Image: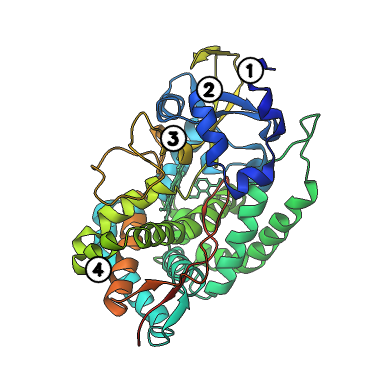
Amino acid sequence: ERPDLAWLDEVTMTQLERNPYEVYERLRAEAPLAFVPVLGSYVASTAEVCREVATSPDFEAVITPAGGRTFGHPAIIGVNGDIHADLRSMVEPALQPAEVDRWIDDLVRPIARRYLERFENDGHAELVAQYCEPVSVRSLGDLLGLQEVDSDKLREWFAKLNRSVTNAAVDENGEFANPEGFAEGDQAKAEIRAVVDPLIDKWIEHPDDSAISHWLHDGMPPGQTRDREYIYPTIYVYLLGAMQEPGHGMASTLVGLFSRPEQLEEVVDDPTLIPRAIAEGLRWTSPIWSATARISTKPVTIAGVDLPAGTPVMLSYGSANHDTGKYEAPSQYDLHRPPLPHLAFGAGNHACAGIYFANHVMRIALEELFEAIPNLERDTREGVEFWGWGFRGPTSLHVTWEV
Ligand code: HEM
Ligand SMILES: COc1cccc(CO)c1O
């Protein structure tokens, strides 16, 4: 429709998944709010527009089309009003900073050690599969009450949900171009139900300290629980993003550090710099790159575009975090970048609920890794490929060290 952006008609889903940064560099200059045909939606690409939409009184949450097809209702990310308030009150207790501080070290550090012990003497490893993902899912899985679900299984589930939720491509008529791509999301949900339904059966009668048990019981009248159909979509939200993203963030941080060997040495020497390293890692390759959205509730003008009521806008926070209006040479990882606001945790009433927890998981994981393997080196025989438009991170991270 917009004539000067006719080139967007030729952007493909595969291109965006392999590397979205060239398209979005053009969008940030040409059209900070732009309709992207293959995505079937307006996309916000700059920090100013993403923050405005995410915080505007004239927008509310909406799930992406493929997200809705996968998760259904009421996913915490796609609802508003009283239901959203209830789901936030449901998830927030275990994520409160004073609560996290009571137990985060005893949760994550033994897990990180357990996975590290399996390879720390090998001289080689693929850190995504052998460390970053397992620590992320085992930590959250235990908190949730999924101790008996193997980390291999939790990792398979968030891979399948990832592909289903980001199966966004639409055809000439605005219909999903790849409908068969939702089948593995449906199969993941069926497997999750088979595992989690018995656990919920038990928690209803025998509550414990698991987070899901508290989701069922907290704030409810005596003898009542939240219906499982009311909480399952948020369970799925967790089994995707909350399981995947801390692993993504640690891995991207390491890749960035490896790209700046002088900076990797600083952080290994001085582990108090790990939080700063992680913050730059999240800006540099945002794990949740473009997975959430808002919808206008009345006619509104954003970045010169007159939007009718009912218009969805995807928030490409990963692009916003490369806004050259804010950052110098944003495509380069720089630990010594001045600490500035970023949008990797979103903004507004639907901003990330688990920031404090996530930052500690990533921190502890990197602390233990650098303690166990101070001479870590990237395996330069294998390149690092990043994949993902909706969620983005490295597909593998081959490293070596002198044993
Ligand atoms: C580095 C790791 C993580 C990153 C980068 C991340 C980022 C985000 C982003 C971008 C959103 C959408 C915000 C928006 O639409 O404005 C979000 C939502 C959310 N995240 Fe995080 N997340 C991470 C880890 C986690 C973890 C571990 C948990 C739970 C233990 C969690 C819980 C949630 C919840 C519940 C929401 C939905 C909030 C709502 O819609 O009201 N996140 N996250
Ligand atoms: C915490 O998990 C998520 C956060 C934001 C988006 C999604 C899925 O679109 C998630 O699963």
Q: Secondary structure at mark 3?
A: helix
Q: Which residue is identified by label 4?
A: 268
Up-down relation of residue 91 to residue 346 (above or below): below
Mark number displayed over residue 30: 2
Labelled pair 2, 3 in contact (Cβ < 8 Å): no
Q: Secondary structure at mark 4?
A: helix
Badge 2 or badge 1: first in the primary sequence: 1
Asked which secondary structure carries label 2, the reply is helix
Q: Split into 4 quadrants, where in the image is the C terminus?
A: bottom left
**Amino acid type shown at disc 4:** Val
- On the question of residue 219 being in view, the answer is no
Q: In the image, is 30 to the left or to the right of 197?
A: left
| Quadrant position of the N terminus in the picture | top right
Q: In the image, residue 326 lies at what x, y percent?
A: 33, 32
Residue type, label 2:
Glu
Q: Seen in the image, is 1 located left or right of residue 80?
A: right
Q: Residues within 10 Å of mark 4 (few under 14, many from 20)?
A: many
**Mark 3 or mark 1, which has the lower sequence index?**
1
In the rendered image, is residue 158 in sight? Answer: yes
Are the residues at dot 2 and dot 1 in contact (C-beta closer than 8 Å)? yes
For marks 2 and 3 on the same chain, the one whose residue lies earlier in the sequence: 2
* Residue nearest the viewer, comparing 89 with 352: 352
The residue to which callout 3 is attached is 320
Of the numbered discs 1 and 4, the one sitting upstream in the chain is: 1
| Residue 100, image quadrant | bottom left
Check disc 1 and give the amino acid type. Answer: Asp
